[PDB]
Length: 231
RNA sequence: CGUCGUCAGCUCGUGCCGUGAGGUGUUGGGUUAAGUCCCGCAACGAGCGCAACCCCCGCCGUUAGUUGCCAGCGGUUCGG
Ligand SMILES: [Mg+2]
Ligand SMILES: [Mg+2]
Ligand SMILES: [Mg+2]
Ligand SMILES: [Mg+2]
Ligand SMILES: [Mg+2]
Ligand SMILES: [Mg+2]
Ligand SMILES: [Mg+2]
Ligand SMILES: [Mg+2]
Ligand SMILES: [Mg+2]
Ligand SMILES: [Mg+2]
Ligand SMILES: [Mg+2]
Ligand SMILES: [Mg+2]
Image (cartoon, rainbow, N blue to C red; front, side):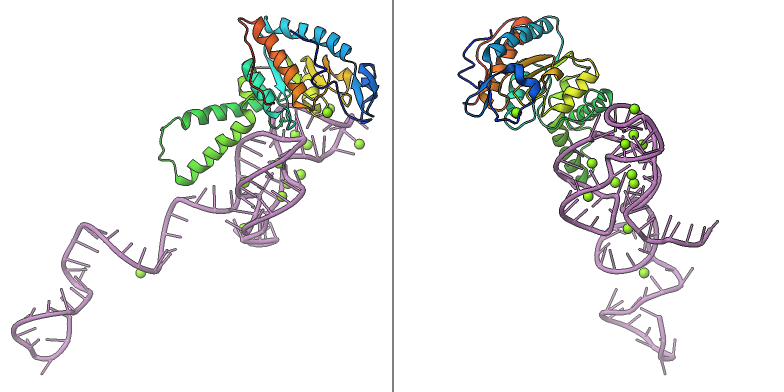
């Protein structure tokens, strides 16, 4: 499912703001820009997707993590396709390490779903309606994707392992495997299954994540053709 | 019971950082009479305080009309 002209969309970036541990995944710096060995990206995807597929057909969740503005929506898109949890907005410390406690906050969201499902007394004061609404709206912003996650994930998918340092550290502290799209400014050794490629351009994120989902959806029953994306 | 002080504060649970005392939260930007509320944040919640629920006063209504009141009509000893 992997394709070959990802060259058409990314082959890496960033001038010498690199992490030396990312050396083995670099071809050269042509424009004064670290360019990624796309053959390495291929070979890695082969190893990585193999892990993904196996995890899919054994029926276990993958928590997709993206928070940078460019990968914001694109992860809500494709993770929804998989029907798998994501965190798009703020990564709340202890989402894994303090799971049960954060999960105490979906119940609130849950209980606000029901209460506002009407009426169960709209005879609650004026000032309260506005409040609890603002609450639900609020809760909705952050726990929208995390609410699907009803128990500790089997692995996580990160768009930027550097940006998402905390998440990488939480999962790792829990022996939960970590798969990641990572460019030259990330730390390879911290990542279990690497996608050495640009993590900034939405194009690359789109290619890698959508095609990642195509692995997920295909392996747990049926398949499907193209998924929503901005040019 | 007094006092600091009606001052806006004092903490806990779990997670995170530290060998450790302990830190974080509770800091930060805005706001309020207020840890008041908003936004942000390795923190996410919870409690005791704050506030509100109570009393008096200020406007109005309903229910009542004496021992209280007297607008209007009668007597009016000349004082509802
Ligand atoms: Mg980057
Ligand atoms: Mg020290
Ligand atoms: Mg320790
Ligand atoms: Mg402490
Ligand atoms: Mg603590
Ligand atoms: Mg304090
Ligand atoms: Mg303190
Ligand atoms: Mg402040
Ligand atoms: Mg005060
Ligand atoms: Mg408060
Ligand atoms: Mg805070
Ligand atoms: Mg009076």
